[PDB]
Image 1 (cartoon, one colour):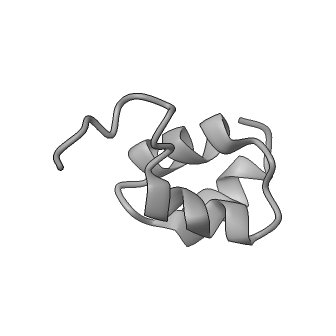
Image 2 (cartoon, helix red, strand yellow):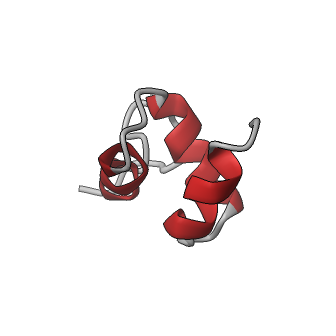
Length: 52
């Protein structure tokens, strides 16, 4: 219906599907990478693989 993207459960669901799609197992890390990237999952892929 209308959950809170904050919780790492949803993991930004779709957004997660993307960072996950690039071979990321750190789900919680995707949700957050997405929150800090405002949707720029690609920008998140490069940064996420970086360190955080």
